[PDB]
Amino acid sequence: HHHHHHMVHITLDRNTANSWLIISKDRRQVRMGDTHQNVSDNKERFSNYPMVLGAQRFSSGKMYWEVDVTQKEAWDLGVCRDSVQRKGQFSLSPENGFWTIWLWQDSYEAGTSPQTTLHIQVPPCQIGIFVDYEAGVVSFYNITDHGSLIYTFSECVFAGPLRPFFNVGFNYSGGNAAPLKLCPL
Ligand SMILES: O=C(COC(F)F)N1C[C@H]2CCC[C@H]2C1
């Protein structure tokens, strides 16, 4: 792909984080803590899952960023509407305002309803995410495999401002403690 020139500097929004997340000082890395991180509750925080949003809001244009997923067993990545549900249980789907892929139990899937199997020969250590607001496109790229396409959501109905979306996953296994990291431009 040739989307690298639309690179944007994403930072994480502490106020949206689940209360167990630890966001680095530079707001570029997030991981699961082993306990509540001693913050007050607020209506923005994802309550049920280890999720956080980027601070940036996008309503036009083309945007690209990269995320490091090295040695994680489980995670979700993509974009979502600014007005997604924060509290209780929900599925990741375009109907609920999410355009995402994930790793879970040694398989990669796109967050369609129902979910779509992905065909990845080279397990990615870094994922590129491209959004074309006007075209209604969200695409995912395998940076470890020379930028190969993973998945394209097209005919997207955003229906609002978009925010970068992250889920570090639970760590029931003890094998999923590693952070998500926003990679330098
Ligand atoms: O955004 C989409 C589909 O495009 C892309 F995601 F593949 N949508 C929005 C959802 C609400 C109506 C049915 C669902 C279709």
Image: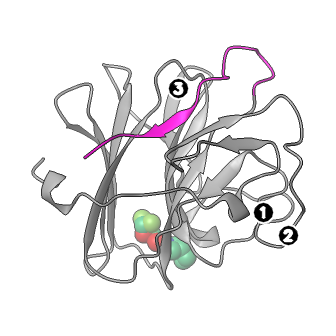
Q: Where residue 15 is drawn, which disc sits there? A: none
Q: What is the x, y in percent for residue 181?
A: 47, 37
Q: CA distance from mark 3 to mark 2?
A: 34 Å
Give above or below for 72 relative to 134.
Answer: above
Check if mark 3's residue and mark 1's residue have beta carbons within 8 Å: no
Relative placement, left or right, of 29 versus 143 is: right
Label 3 element class: strand
Relative placement, left or right, of 43 versus 124 is: right
Relative placement, left or right, of 40 versus 185 is: right
Q: What residue is rendered at 89% in x and 48% in y?
A: 38
Relative placement, left or right, of 3 versus 59 is: left
Part of the protein shown in magenta: 171-185
Q: Residues within 10 Å of mark 3 (few under 14, many from 20)?
A: some
Label 1 element class: loop
* Label 3 vs label 2, nearer the camera: 2
User: How many numbered callouts?
Assistant: 3
Q: What is the x, y in percent for residue 73?
A: 60, 22
Q: What is the x, y in percent for residue 110?
A: 48, 46
Q: Is mark 3 within 8 Å of ligand 1?
A: no
Q: What residue is rendered at 75% in x and 32% in y?
A: 170
Check if mark 1's residue and mark 2's residue have beta carbons within 8 Å: yes
Label 2 element class: loop
Residue hosting label 2: 42
Of callouts 3 and 2, the N-terminal one: 2
Residue hosting label 1: 45
Q: Nearer the viewer, residue 40 or 115?
A: 40
Tell whether position 174 is magenta: yes
Residue hosting label 3: 107
Q: CA distance from mark 1 to mark 2?
A: 6 Å
Single out the residue that lies furthest toward the left: 2
